[PDB]
Image: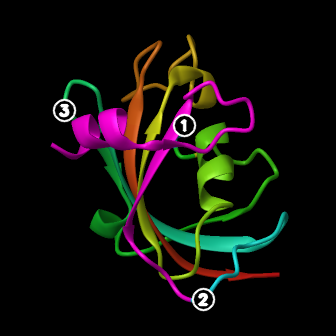
Amino acid sequence: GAPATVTEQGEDITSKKDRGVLKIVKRVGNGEETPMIGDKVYVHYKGKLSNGKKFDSSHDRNEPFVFSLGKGQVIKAWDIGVATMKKGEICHLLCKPEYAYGSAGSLPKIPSNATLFFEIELLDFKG
Amino acid sequence: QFPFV
């Protein structure tokens, strides 16, 4: 399924080239521009753990998730991955723990040392 | 608080 596919067939988008964050573009977005640091970004997401559990989804809450890009408000994999997206893009990300919650985890749904899968839609970005 | 931090 999708998590296996992005594990095996995703592109490393890290600066380190340590395969910590892999990406597949699922729906090509609009034009060429990507957001800049500090922009307000609006995303829809779904997240799965490596054991198949769907641990979170913005769609189920009927509101997007909004954060300021590149400020460390979210896991490193999201700062990295959303910065590569166009408006209207849908991508899959596979996040090793170093770019997510590491050995700490995140109570209550994310265990220690968790590799995470996400599907992310970039709805909009504004300065 | 995922999605924070």
Under mark 1, the amino acid is Val
Secondary structure under tag 2 reads loop
Q: Quadrant of residue A24?
A: bottom left
Structural crowding at the residue carrying mark 2, measured as other residues with C-alpha within 10 Å and reported as few (<14), some (14–19) or many (≥20): few
Q: Which residue position holds label 1?
A: A21
Q: Are marks 2 and 3 on the same chain?
A: yes
Residue A54 in view in this figure = no
Q: What is the number of the mark on residue A31?
A: 2
- Range shown magenta: A1-30
Under mark 3, the amino acid is Gly
Q: Which residue is found at the position 66% from the left and 30% from the top?
A: A17
- Which is more toward the observer, A12 or A101? A12
Q: Are marks 1 and 2 in contact (CB under 8 Å)?
A: no
Q: What is the number of the mark on residue A52?
A: 3
Whether A115 is drawn above or below A41: the answer is above
Mark 2 falls within which chain?
A
Separation (CA) of disc 1 from disc 2: 24 Å
Mark 3 falls within which chain?
A
Provide residue A119's location: percent of width, then percent of height.
Answer: 37, 56
**Looking at the image, is mark 1 or mark 2 earlier in the sequence?**
1
Provide residue A81's location: percent of width, then percent of height.
Answer: 59, 52
Q: Which residue is found at the position 55% from the left and 28% from the top?
A: A19
Q: Which residue is found at the position 58% from the left and 76% from the top?
A: A86
Extreme residue toward the bottom, this view = A31
Whether A123 is drawn above or below A59: the answer is below
